[PDB]
Amino acid sequence: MDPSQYASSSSWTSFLKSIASFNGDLSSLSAPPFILSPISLTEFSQYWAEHPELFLEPSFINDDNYKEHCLIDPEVESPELARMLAVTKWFISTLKSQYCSRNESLGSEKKPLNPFLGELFVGKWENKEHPEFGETVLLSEQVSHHPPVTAFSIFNDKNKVKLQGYNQIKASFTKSLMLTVKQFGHTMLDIKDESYLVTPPPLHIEGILVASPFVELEGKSYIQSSTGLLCVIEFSGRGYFSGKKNSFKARIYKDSKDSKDKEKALYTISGQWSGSSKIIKANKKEESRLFYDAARIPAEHLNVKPLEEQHPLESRKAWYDVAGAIKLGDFNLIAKTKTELEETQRELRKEEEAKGISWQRRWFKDFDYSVTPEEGALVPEKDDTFLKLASALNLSTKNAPSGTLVGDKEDRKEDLSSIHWRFQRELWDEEKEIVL
Ligand SMILES: CC(C)CCC[C@@H](C)[C@H]1CC[C@H]2[C@@H]3[C@@H](O)C=C4C[C@@H](O)CC[C@]4(C)[C@H]3CC[C@]12C
Image 1 (cartoon, rainbow, N blue to C red):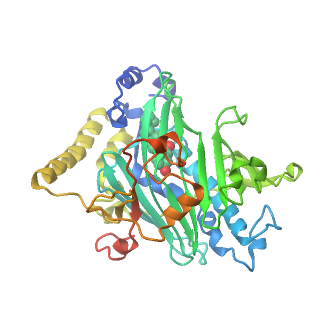
Image 2 (image 1 turned 180 degrees about the horizontal axis):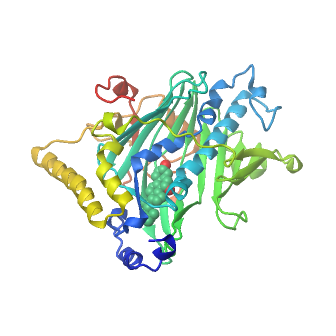
Image 3 (image 1 turned 90 degrees about the vertical axis):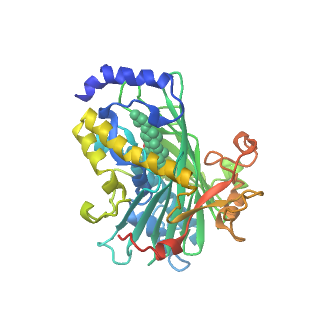
């Protein structure tokens, strides 16, 4: 049917009613075929680097050229600061990919495919137009199905730029049908020997009543560097802070302590992350300059090998039948193909339980950061990067919502674990079946 017919359709009305008895599992929702996406959530990891040049820019900045690598401030104070500005621009550039991609390609935000345990999604940005860039690899794996957890790593060996992280959410509906989403997990970005800890922000899905869902960000995201510098990004929508949706304000401070006082902000960036934003140095409001304009920079999608040569665990190959049915809009075929895949998984799990066998994650392992780790679990190293960056930011290391600070209510939650997924490069190095 035409989108103008969605809101009043029998299907949408039945869907809205299923929300009333929502059990916390988004998959229990009877989402009509027209609001279904043929893309699995394991693919979302690619959204962290769809702008190759921005992802790699920090690695080209050094003590001998940093002032030549800071468009908004040729008189930038230091290379560490020029790199924090570059990392900040990269982070901002990821937002349109992360949260607006489906509105563009599907017509609105839609229900993504719930990944199966073990699902993989791999590819690479060949960066053929920039030989100095080199190849950038994306590895994404579904390390958990109950609940859904996606772990990932994107790395550029040539320039020594590597990123890793994982993600999971907890959703619930308000009485007004707003879908509140809290993200969990964090992402770490290494630029040679310099490190950055990034925390995703919470968000809500608007437009559910009118059947035209879309994402709006809220709360805060942090970018804590090993250099001490810290960027605090605050998100707002419609009005409140800005008069336009998808707005934000980011401030860079010399350190976590200085972030308590907004006046100590070295720079202040503001505007829309899906559009244009300006930057002001110190309090020199009269000297604002264009920081980023998402409309001028086309996203670059990674290269994925053809279906014919994909491993059975690779997302697109495994979901092929379901994706085809969804694109066709065939109610029965969608149910049939989805059940076939999911029922096979269920049988697999039941067998593992009966045979006393466990699913082994391929490239990621869960590290127990708790003071009282499970006897068989892996424990973090001495100079763990996350530990020091989280300490500098005073970020909680527990499995609390992303961005939770030590002392916050979420951090004082009783019996809350502190297990985090970590990429094991060695495991990819000795990979025997998967290729790019
Ligand atoms: C849309 C509605 C009909 C059903 C509910 C869909 C809901 C579960 C989807 C829709 C938006 C999805 C977000 C997506 O906006 C972007 C990201 C960023 C990525 O890094 C991690 C996943 C996440 C949070 C998606 C989770 C699933 C969401 C909320």
